[PDB]
Image 1: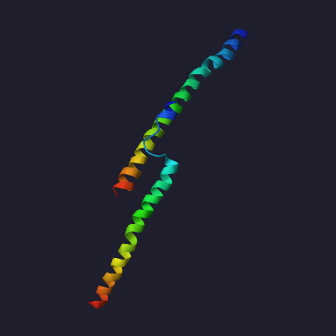
Image 2 (image 1 turned 180 degrees about the vertical axis):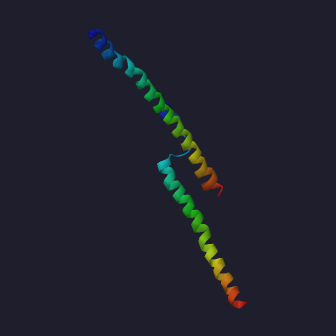
Image 3 (image 1 turned 135 degrees about the horizontal axis):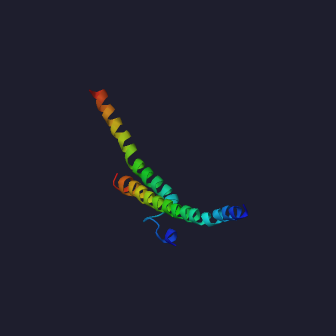
Length: 49
Length: 53
């Protein structure tokens, strides 16, 4: 019953897999395209040098 | 000879209980270690990587 009641806090590991997949994919999607746009502007500045 | 045979026969049956308890308690100790690992890994994923990072 301890093994049925002493579960660690938060949603379990098999659910934590898609939890971390969703969180890391939204973290990447919010930032990587912004980095690409920044690099495009920066290389525009490089060719304007 | 037959007293020795009977004693050696009963020795294993009297023995097996303590290895049964030994494997049971080490099996529960494995569950405790796995629970501690699960807590540490969920701390590493959620607290250290998912939310803060």
